[PDB]
Amino acid sequence: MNIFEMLRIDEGLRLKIYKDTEGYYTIGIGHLLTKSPSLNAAKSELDKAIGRNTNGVITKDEAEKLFNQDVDAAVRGILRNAKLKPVYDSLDAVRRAAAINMVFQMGETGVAGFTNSLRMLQQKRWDEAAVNLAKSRWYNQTPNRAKRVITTARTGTWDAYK
Ligand SMILES: [Cl-]
Ligand SMILES: [Cl-]
């Protein structure tokens, strides 16, 4: 298991513009296109992202390209973030995959927020970070995926994904 296969499971793959859980226009593997209510602002964002006139439809390859750029951007957002980096640097490789999952889904600003959990993760207080992470909108909105990420953080194993 790795961060790519982990996220591919959690986000699925979709070759046509679609709406995410929050109602936002998305495509491929969890690639947010826009928060605007326009299928047209979205077809616009999509085209600019792909470099061609897609008509709201992309291939596996294009989707994978987006995916790769987004995992890359999550990692880099973590490493640049003064709040995130040290927590991240302190973790093992499995747990790191979890942090990355969180960032890809909710953005660096969101996670950077989770102050208390961050502190407990760093202190390697596993059970408690898991309890605190659950007290969030995130968990309440997408509980099964959140449970998977949270077990990954708690345990340091890929159990939840096998
Ligand atoms: Cl992009
Ligand atoms: Cl879910």
Image: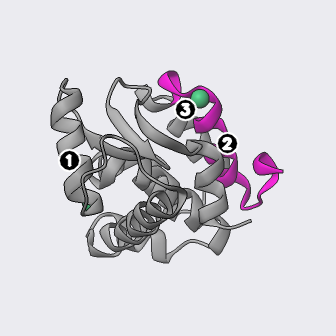
Question: Three-letter amino acid code at disc 2?
Answer: Arg
Q: Picture quarter containing residue 33? A: top left
The residues colored magenta run 139-162
Q: Quadrant of the N terminus?
A: bottom right
Q: Secondary structure at mark 1?
A: helix
Q: Residues within 10 Å of mark 1 (few under 14, many from 20)?
A: some
> Which residue matches tag 3?
134
Q: Nearer the viewer, residue 10 or 34?
A: 34
Q: Earlier in the sequence, mark 3 or mark 1?
A: 1
User: Mark 3 CB in 8 Å range of ligand 2?
Assistant: no
Q: Position of residue 141 (x, y in %)?
A: 48, 23
User: Mark 1 CB in 8 Å range of ligand 1?
Assistant: no
Whether label 2 touches label 3, CB < 8 Å? no
Distance, label 2 to label 3, CA atoms, is: 11 Å
> Which residue matches tag 2?
148
Q: Picture quarter containing residue 76? A: bottom left
| Principal secondary structure, stretch drawn in magenta | helix
Instruction: From the viewer's perspective, tell me whether residue 131 is left or right of residue 99.
Output: right
* Label disc, if present, on residue 45 of the rendered structure: 1
Distance, label 2 to label 1, CA atoms, is: 31 Å
Task: Tell me which colouring the rendered structure shows.
Answer: one colour
* Label disc, if present, on residue 72 of the rendered structure: none
Quadrant location, ligand no. 2: top right
Question: Three-letter amino acid code at disc 1?
Answer: Glu
Q: Secondary structure at mark 2?
A: helix
Q: Nearer the viewer, residue 18 or 52?
A: 52
Q: Residue at x 58, y 64 (%)?
A: 97
Question: Three-letter amino acid code at disc 3?
Answer: Ala
